[PDB]
Image (tube, rainbow, N blue to C red):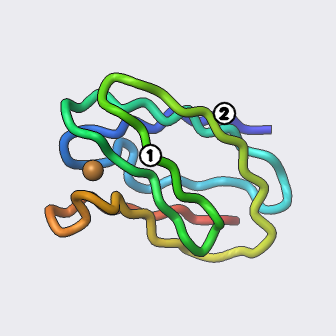
């Protein structure tokens, strides 16, 4: 239903606020354009994906509950590598 590219950079997400539709499928193209390994982790949406430097992971999600969900990189959270996903 929706396709969204998300860049994983050293050390931030772009975009770092992502809005996706409730009860519909969204494909996320997770592209690591950084030199470091990064993750795209949203525990409350059941997502936890590692993306190596220069590589890509493509996932399709279908969230059932409206809300705002914290997105983190497990490796660089403390450096501010964080964002959110709004399901609406
Ligand atoms: Cu990271």
Residue at point 45% right, 71% down?
Answer: 70
Secondary structure state at the residue bearing disc 2: strand
Distance from label 1 to label 2 (Cα)? 19 Å
Crowd class of label 1 (few under 14; some 14 to 19; many from 20; radius 10 Å):
some
Please identify the quarter of the rendering in which residue 44 is found: bottom right
Q: Residue 25: x, y in percent?
A: 80, 46
Tag 1 residue: 50
Tag 2 residue: 3
Residue 55 position (above or below residue 75): above
Please identify the quarter of the rendering in which residue 76 is found: bottom left
Residue at far left of view: 79
Instruction: Classify residue 6 as left or right of residue 28.
Output: left
Instruction: Classify residue 21 as left or right of residue 83.
Output: right
User: Quarter of the image containing the N terminus?
Assistant: top right
Q: Residue 50: x, y in percent?
A: 44, 46
Residue at far top of view: 54
- Which numbered disc covers residue 18? none
Residue 31 position (above or below residue 88): above
Front of the two marks 1 and 2 = 1
């Amino acid at each position: 239903a929706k396709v969204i590219e998300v860049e994983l950079n050293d050390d931030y997400f772009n975009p770092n606020v992502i809005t996706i539709p409730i009860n519909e499928s969204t494909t996320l193209l997770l592209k690591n354009k950084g030199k470091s390994e990064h993750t795209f982790t949203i525990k409350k949406l059941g997502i936890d994906v590692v993306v190596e430097s220069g590589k890509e992971k493509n996932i399709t999600v279908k969230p059932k509950s409206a809300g705002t969900y914290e997105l983190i990189c497990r490796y660089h959270l403390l450096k501010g590598m964080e964002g959110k996903v709004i399901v609406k």
